[PDB]
Structures are given as structure tokens and as C-alpha cells.
Image: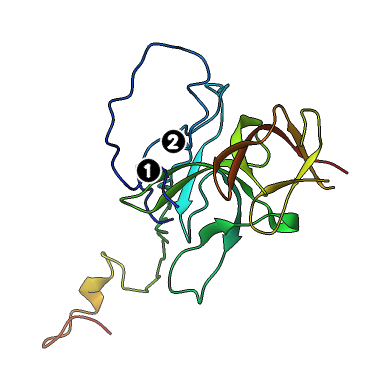
């Protein structure tokens, strides 16, 4: 529910090895990032971190927001959150993305689609291919390296 | 649009637009014609109390 662990740790983390130190929930952004990527931000409704987002509209008093969602309403991928301001960094669905995303509770090369809650699931209208296997971080939190190529016909 | 909140990384920023307006003022020229007595002829119309027919 939080980008960083909510409870403080009690142990100094030894930094000796250099392998498999990136399979954490705090890894924001993408593994490969271009300096020509288009980056937006929107007010967040809920916690859409590491999830696909859609646009949500209220009465009309306040501006639009982004909420976790997929299907035919998919607008992009949320890659970072600023908690103080409620800001959600969004990469549009028309821009290539490669990074770790939340997976529904799967082998590399398997086609993926975003479900109603913005979670990737194995297969229809979006190009998403898993580049690794599901890594479990919590009882109900599974992440996976995926690449999004846009919408298919 | 509403301003952009500068948090973490962002490229898409709200924009301030500009416009120009041209105001034109028209000036029109008009003329009138009037009839009077001739200079040399006024002497024959210089009545005792007034000048003119």
C-alpha cells in the first residue's frame, strides 16, 4: 500500500553482493529508460503504484484523476508516486515502457493483459509480454518484468 | 489550464497562451458649399445699416 516499507527496519543492510538487489517494491521507474520518454503526472485516487491507470471524472468541481484500472479504459502505466502531494507519474500507453509491474495472484514470453484493477494477467487488446517470472514480495504482492508495446488490433 | 505540480519527474507542463488584437480607426473627409457676394460687388450692397442683400 506504500511505495516504501511503512514500518522501519531493525537491521543494517549489508551491501556486498551486486546481484538480485533490484527485486524490491521501491524500485520506481523502468529498467531501461530513454531521455526522450514522455512523462505526465496526475492527482491519484487510491494507490495506483506499479499498476495500469485510467481517467476518473467526478462531479466537475475538481479536475480529473487517475485510478487503477485496465480493459478498454487503459490510459497508461503509473511508475512513481509522490506521497506528499498525491502525485502519480504516468507513462502514456502510446510510449514504450520496460519495467517491473504488479501481477495478479507465468513464464517469460507469455502474453499479458491488464485486468480491471490494473494488474497484469495471462491471456487481447494490449501488447504486454512477460520478460521474467513472478517474484513474490508479499502474500498477495507479485511483481513481474514486463514490456508494453501499445494496443493491438 | 491549471498549473502543473512539480513532483518527481514530469515533462508535460501546462501552457500560457498569447493573442494579439488590431484596432483600426477610420477618418472621413466631408465638405460643404456656400454662396456669397463678390468682393468687388459688395460696394453696391453696402446698405446704410447693414452690408449684404
Q: Is residue A15 left or right of residue A55?
A: left
Position of A75 relative to A148 (above/below): below
Residue at screen point 38% across, 37% down: B8
Q: Is residue A121 left or right of residue A14?
A: right
Task: State whether discs 2 and 1 lie on one chain.
Answer: yes
* Nearest to the observer: residue B15 or residue A80: A80
Chain ID for label 1?
A: A
Position of A38 relative to A52 (above/below): above
Label disc, if present, on residue A32 of the rendered structure: none
Residue at screen point 50% across, 25% down: A22
Q: Quadrant of residue B47?
A: bottom left
- Residue A130: image location, x then y, percent: 73, 32
Badges 2 and 1: C-beta atoms under 8 Å apart? yes
Find disc 2 in the rendering and name its residue: A26
* Nearest to the observer: residue A18 or residue A129: A18
Task: Report the residue that reaches farthest toward the right.
Answer: A153
Position of B52 relative to A123 (above/below): below
Q: Quadrant of residue B31?
A: bottom left
Residue at screen point 58% across, 50% down: A140
Quadrant into which the C terminus of chain A falls: top right
Label disc, if present, on residue A5 of the rendered structure: 1
* Nearest to the observer: residue A60 or residue A114: A114
- Residue A6: image location, x then y, percent: 34, 48
- Residue A24: image location, x then y, percent: 48, 32
* Nearest to the observer: residue A138 or residue A153: A138
Circle 2: element type: loop
Task: Report the residue that reaches farthest toward the left.
Answer: B49
Residue at screen point 26% across, 64% down: B40
- Residue A119: image location, x then y, percent: 65, 50
**Label 1: few (<14), some or many (≥20) within 10 Å?**
few
Task: Report the residue that reaches farthest toward the front.
Answer: A11
Amino acid at each position: 500500500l506504500m511505495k516504501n516499507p511503512q514500518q522501519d527496519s531493525g537491521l543494517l543492510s549489508n551491501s556486498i553482493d551486486f546481484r538480485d538487489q533490484n527485486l524490491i517494491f521501491s524500485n520506481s521507474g523502468g529498467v531501461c529508460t530513454s531521455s526522450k520518454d514522455k512523462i505526465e503526472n496526475y492527482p491519484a485516487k487510491g494507490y495506483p503504484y506499479k499498476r495500469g491507470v485510467k481517467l476518473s471524472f467526478g462531479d466537475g468541481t475538481t479536475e480529473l484523476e487517475v485510478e487503477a484500472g485496465g480493459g478498454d479504459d487503459l490510459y497508461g502505466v503509473c511508475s512513481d508516486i509522490d506521497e506528499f502531494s498525491g502525485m502519480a507519474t504516468v507513462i502514456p500507453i502510446t510510449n514504450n515502457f520496460t519495467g517491473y509491474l504488479t501481477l495478479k495472484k507465468v513464464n517469460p514470453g507469455d502474453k499479458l493483459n491488464f485486468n480491471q484493477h490494473g494488474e497484469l494477467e495471462k491471456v487481447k487488446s494490449v501488447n504486454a509480454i512477460a520478460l521474467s517470472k513472478a517474484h513474490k514480495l508479499t502474500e498477495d504482492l507479485f511483481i513481474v518484468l514486463a514490456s508494453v508495446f501499445g494496443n493491438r488490433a | 489550464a491549471n498549473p502543473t505540480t512539480i513532483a518527481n519527474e514530469v515533462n508535460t507542463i501546462s501552457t500560457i497562451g498569447f493573442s494579439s488584437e488590431v484596432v483600426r480607426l477610420n477618418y472621413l473627409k466631408l465638405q460643404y458649399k456656400f454662396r456669397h457676394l463678390k468682393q468687388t460687388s459688395e460696394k453696391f450692397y453696402t446698405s446704410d445699416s447693414y452690408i449684404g442683400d
